[PDB]
Each structure stands twice: as C-alpha cells, then as structure tokens.
Amino acid sequence: CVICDPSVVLALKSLEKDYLPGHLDAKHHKAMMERVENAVKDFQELSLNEDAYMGVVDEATLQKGSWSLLKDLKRITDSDVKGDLFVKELFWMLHLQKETFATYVARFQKEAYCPNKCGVMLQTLIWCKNCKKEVHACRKSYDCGERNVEVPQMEDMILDCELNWHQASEGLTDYSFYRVWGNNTETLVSKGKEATLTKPMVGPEDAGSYRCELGSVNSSPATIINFHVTVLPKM
Ligand SMILES: *[C@@H]1O[C@H](CO)[C@@H](O)[C@H](O)[C@H]1NC(C)=O
C-alpha cells in the first residue's frame, strides 16, 4: 500500500526524471520505470503466511513502509551506480522491501489491527488497492478488567484510565471520573482530556469504588474502567 504515499510517488518521478538520464541507457528508461511502478504497486499483493491478509493498513504502517523503501532507494542514488550494477541493485532492493513491508503488515495485523482488548476503538484504516481511507469500529467487551488499587495511608492515589490504544483512536471526547458510593449511586468527580485522577495524600474515606468513562462523539463510551481502592493504614 506504500504507493498511497505522495512522497513515494514523487521519489519515483524523480528517479525517472533526475536519476535515469545519467545512470541507465535510455532504451531501458520507459521499460524499467514501467517495471518499477508495477513492482511498488505490487506491495499491496501480499500472502502473509498465517493469518490471512485483509488489504488494510493503518497510516503508521504505511509510513513505516515508505520510509524503509525510500531510504533504501536513496542509498542507491547516493552511490551513483550506473548500468547493470544499478539495475541489479535497484531490483534486489525492491524485492527485499516488499518482503520487509509484508512483515510490517503482518506485525500490524498481529498487534496494531483492532488492538483493543475491550471497549470500542475507532481506527482509521487505509485500503491498499484504492488508497482509500475509512474508519472502522473495533468493538470488544466492556470489561477492561477490574483495577484493584492498594494505596498507603497518606500517599497519592493515582487512577489511570489510559490504555495504549486510546492515542490511536478517533472520536474521543473526555475522560469522566465517577465516585461510586455504596448507595449504588455516584458523583462526577472529574472531566476533561486528562486520562488520570489524582487525589493526593489520600485518607481512609477516600477508599472505595471509582469509575472512569471515556466518551466518543457522539455515542456510547469508548472505555469503561472500574477501580476498587483500598487504603492501607501503613508506611
Ligand atoms: C450515597 O451514599 C454516600 C455515603 O457516604 C453519601 O455520601 C451520599 O450522600 C449518598 N447519596 C445521597 C443521594 O445522599
């Protein structure tokens, strides 16, 4: 999918126009550039071993692959290699970079694709084949796992509602921190773009149940996390 990057396109249009004139006989120009353009488009034809390949990457994986490629391409052109050497070098590199990209896409699916273990992530994906950008909802369980927090008598109580995937999600609004009373009732304690809640130098009253919601425009919460806080009469 790496031809979806405007930079890759120009670097190709620079190889043809700036590099080929002084480093390959003109008989090979149209033919080899025909082959190069086709090779790079073929970055989207992937097999992937197992699991199967979906035809989507996130924008990071896409950038990642364009970088590998264009740094490699560039090494060649700083080298000033000509003729046959140049063609071999050029075509080894394309071959390696495809295989490399393949490993990006594989890693992307195993680890970056709908990476959330709970909640609902809005992931911006891109379709290899048409360079088209979509937003896809990864909907998982609402159970992020219960956070049991032990905090010493008079130290800070930090409640972190941040998940690693939150920074990669679309449509987030605010984190709202609730206090749950035992009444099966609650009070809004905090709300903003802060992912944490700190009641410093806490005390025995401050123990109990807390709750974090992460909102999304404009619908159901992206994340719910529950904390149970127990304060310890201790050092
Ligand atoms: C619910 O229980 C807590 C217990 O401390 C209390 O502070 C709160 O006022 C109760 N709810 C209402 C509506 O009073």
Image (spheres, rainbow, N blue to C red):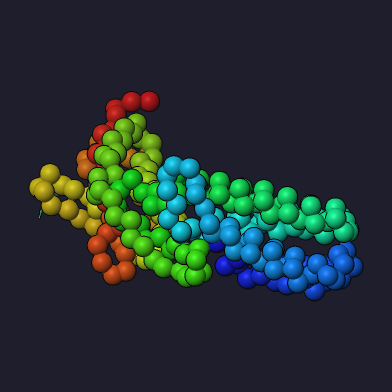
Q: Is 45 situated left or right of 184 in this image?
A: right
Report whether 103 appears left or right of 224.
right
Where does the image place residue 176, in percent across and percent down from the top left? 30, 57
Given residues 181 and 153, the one toward you in this image is 181
**Does residue 206 appear in this view?**
no
Q: Position of residue 64 (x, y in %)?
A: 60, 55
Quarter of the rendering containing residue 4: bottom right
Position of residue 89 in the picture relative to residue 171 (left or right): right
Picture mark count: 0
Left of 48 or right of it: where is 21? right
Q: Residue furthest left?
A: 183
Please tell me which residue is depicted at 26% across the width and 39% down the height of the picture: 146
Which residue is painted at 47% across and 64% down in the image?
127
Report x, y in % for residue 55. Answer: 46, 59
Tell me the residue at 79%/69% (across/down).
29
Q: Position of residue 54 (x, y in %)?
A: 42, 55
- 115 in relation to 193, above or below: above
